[PDB]
Image (tube, rainbow, N blue to C red):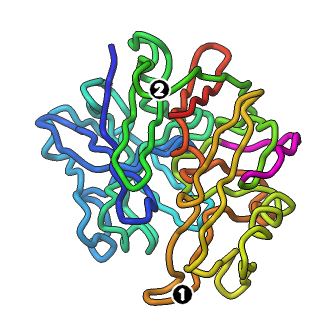
Amino acid sequence: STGSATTTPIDSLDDAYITPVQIGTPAQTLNLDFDTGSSDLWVFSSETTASEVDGQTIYTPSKSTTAKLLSGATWSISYGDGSSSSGDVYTDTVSVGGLTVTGQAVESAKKVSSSFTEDSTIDGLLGLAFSTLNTVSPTQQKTFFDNAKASLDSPVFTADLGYHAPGTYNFGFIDTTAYTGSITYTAVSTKQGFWEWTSTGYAVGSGTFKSTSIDGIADTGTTLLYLPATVVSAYWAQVSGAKSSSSVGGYVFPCSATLPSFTFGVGSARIVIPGDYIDFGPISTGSSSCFGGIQSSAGIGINIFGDVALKAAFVVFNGATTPTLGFASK
């Protein structure tokens, strides 16, 4: 089998992407944030504290003839941005772009933190990291991809995120019309539960490429590109007036600037992030200070190839017995 679904930016900045997902019988369609940095499929629901729902579409398990309470199971997750959610668990039929999994764990939120409530466009998350990170207790649950894998034509999914435009998540096949050149594959460590890999270096604008190993994760659920402070300083030093602002929480730059590109290495290959992809707009409405899309990872503990980086590439998440990642230009 295969599946193919369009993913759409939630706003004019590409802060996140939503993909429609069918849950239950008859189908209830919710728009989920596909997150290769986590491993829980959770949804706003009829069980979510009413004051914490503000415009989201909810899953109502009592209206699904295929929903079954997973008795005793609870979940609770905290994300790198400080947000969180928790609740109980049903199994139900879940379909993405025509690909159907029966018996998928659907984690129903009883509580969500303020940032989820405040984002009316995201009805939940669909985790695509390794199932060892799934938070369901006392019986850990499998991701949608893990459950679908055996049925897929090939044990892969691909992320093709758009810049200010829709893109595609494909399951079970590699669309050879969606990229240019060849796909370069690189080794993955699953030891932390992430799609963790090592970039071979970077360049800023038209500058020379610096060969240096940068271990990080391919994370569709993180907006920006988080890299070591040395790399980030070298980038922003090429932008007149750019500075790191403790009060804002990162590098800012004059909105009048034209930003240089940023290149990262994948083996001997190179992915170029255009400068415009690094502009996240005014820090507050009407400000002439703009927020940068490349930020330091120094306070995180891990480097994160988030949407800013991934949207410049066609990305293969290869879930073969030994997982690997593939990157192509597009």
> Magenta residues?
206-217
* Residue carrying label 1: 288
Name the side, left or right, on which 94 lies relative to 189: left
Above or below, 266 relative to 257: above
Question: Is 13 one of the magenta-colored residues?
Answer: no
Q: Nearer the viewer, residue 286 or 136?
A: 286
Residue depicted at x 46% and y 62%: 15
The type of residue carrying mark 2 is Phe
Name the side, left or right, on which 32 lies relative to 262: left
* Residue carrying label 2: 157
Q: Position of residue 131 (x, y in %)?
A: 56, 33
Q: Position of residue 269 (x, y in %)?
A: 71, 29
Sequence-wise first label, 1 or 2 = 2
The type of residue carrying mark 1 is Ser
Label 2 residue SS: strand
In the drawing, what numbered circle is on residue 312?
none
Q: Nearer the viewer, residue 43 or 222?
A: 222
Q: Position of residue 204 (x, y in %)?
A: 75, 54
Label 1 residue SS: loop
Q: Quadrant of residue 10?
A: bottom left
Cα distance between the residues tagged 1 and 2: 40 Å
